Picture 1 (tube, protein in one colour):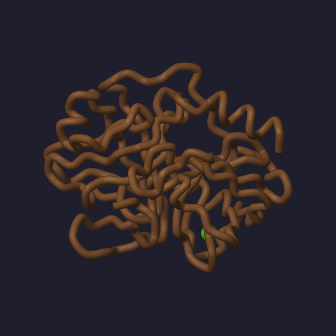
Picture 2 (cartoon, chains in turn purple, green):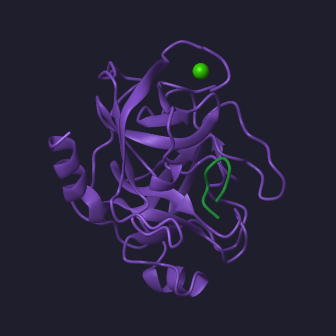
Length: 223
Length: 8
Ligand SMILES: [Ca+2]
């Protein structure tokens, strides 16, 4: 997260870190055994780290739970990043508590200008890299489809939205992928991609979770 | 680029 702020430990209790011996993506806990992340975060060897704040220190409240299923959307296209959503089933249910909590899925899509909280342990620099220890947060609005499509012509599918700040300086960034964009208490986005981070006129692009709620539910229900 | 570590 570039231009964000330290969330505060466990203030984003649905935020998970996907760890493969290092944090590589975020995710969002959507029930005690399932995490939503980005399809492009798929890999083997995912350990979901819940309850994290400082991802480099065991502070307490962590739950590390291996992914037992990592379900990339069947129609994920790694070139276009359409359907950039993955469900991770935890090998065992997380113990939910105030610091490890699911986030609700949308019941409907969010509107342009809705303010959302985007969080993650991604790079905090728009140039170069600095990976934070603690979870960073960014309040960011959903942009209009027209602005999103203007920023990324031909690249924004119906399963994407832009959020953030065209003036630059505030965005999700590498390492935030897969993590949440929560708006009005609903997981409306998954950090997916963007041109750089926090670059002028290049807002973050996010998987539009509301398009996947049924798929999520159906996939969870069948797994 | 995707926002994973590493970006893709
Ligand atoms: Ca920790």
